[PDB]
Image: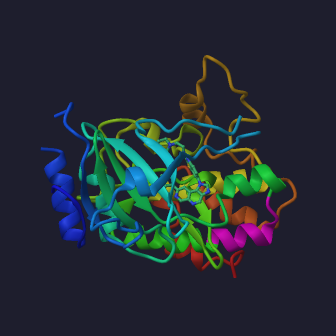
Amino acid sequence: LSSVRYGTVEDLLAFANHISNFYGQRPQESGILLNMVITPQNGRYQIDSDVLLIPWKLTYRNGSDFIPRGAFGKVYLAQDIKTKKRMACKLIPVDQFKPSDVEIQACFRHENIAELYGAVLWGETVHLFMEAGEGGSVLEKLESCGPMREFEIIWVTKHVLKGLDFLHSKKVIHHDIKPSNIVFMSTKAVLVDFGLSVQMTEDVYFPKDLRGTEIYMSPEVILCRGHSTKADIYSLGATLIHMQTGTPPWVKRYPRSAYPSYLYIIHKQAPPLEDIADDCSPGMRELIEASLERNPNHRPRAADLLKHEALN
Ligand SMILES: c1ccc(-c2cc3c(cn2)ncc2ncn(-c4ccc5nc(NCCN6CCOCC6)sc5c4)c23)cc1
């Protein structure tokens, strides 16, 4: 409350609720750390003096760069100067900070999901220290070495589906599955960015605002008339197209302009079966076109997709 301390998920959530309930006062540290990732100095965790914070920007070279709708804050690369340990840092202001920004990552832990290390308030900014992938993002790999080979896609898709299956079993819709939100580790691929993620109360989720990245959006998400976890499956299909072609589903056929109409194009023409790569196995084609299925009730679950012939 007055200083940064080590705590539980309960301590973390109690702090998040207090922040959501005064500028010009001396900036003092306060918050809860779930993991001991910041080296203390004189019995304090002084992130302003001991944590190296630099903006984390991705170099986009293909128009494969879409700003997420309803997104807030900034992504920074945080590094504890003493241990030289790298972490991701989601910087959110006090007024915009609410308990949903941490709830998913703090309560639901899985191998294919990025771990939440803690939340530190310093002045007017709340710092969300998270697990970082030492091997970069899927987008970085695509922009660097070009379109991915089928075996490399199968390896990533197997890991992504395990993380989706987990979140979908806990009734959580990720809402932003894109190559930039899938990162590489030494033995796995992990899902990041839980800012747009919601926990489902009932069988159908009714959004108040249109949130997410437009090119990977399903036809039911654009409509805002209700959707479920199946929305993430369409987005996976859209990322699968991005992985094998080097560009997301609609960008090539319908170029980028100051007057875009992608929400209309997806609604009138989805699934993007024309954007699927010409040189891909019949099994892999079958996997993509089923995940892009127009009707969410006829689209497979993450558990069904893991059992597919292409992956095995
Ligand atoms: C939120 C919190 C943490 C991460 C994150 C990124 C990682 C990582 C672990 N975690 N491990 C390795 C890695 N190699 C590159 N990246 C990387 C770096 C920056 C980056 N920015 C992205 N999006 C820009 C849009 N912002 C707008 C504000 O709201 C959030 C989204 S995706 C993205 C991905 C990463 C991502 C988002």
Query: Can you say which quadrant of the picture contains the C terminus?
Result: bottom right
Residue, far bottom = 312
Q: Main secondary structure of the magenta part?
A: helix
Going 19% across and 36% down the picture, which residue do you hit? 25
Q: Dividing the picture into quarters, in which one does residue 248 lie?
A: top right
Magenta stretch in the rendered image: 148-157
Going 31% across and 55% down the picture, which residue do you hit? 120
In this picture, residue 183 sits left or right of residue 3:
right
Query: Observer-nearest residue: 100 or 203?
Result: 100
Query: Can you say which quadrant of the picture contains the N terminus?
Result: bottom left
Residue 204 location (% of width, % of height): 31, 54
Residue, far right = 279
Q: Is residue 204 visible?
A: no
With respect to residue 125, does 41 lie above or below? below
Going 68% across and 52% down the picture, which residue do you hit? 139
Query: Observer-nearest residue: 310 or 259?
Result: 259
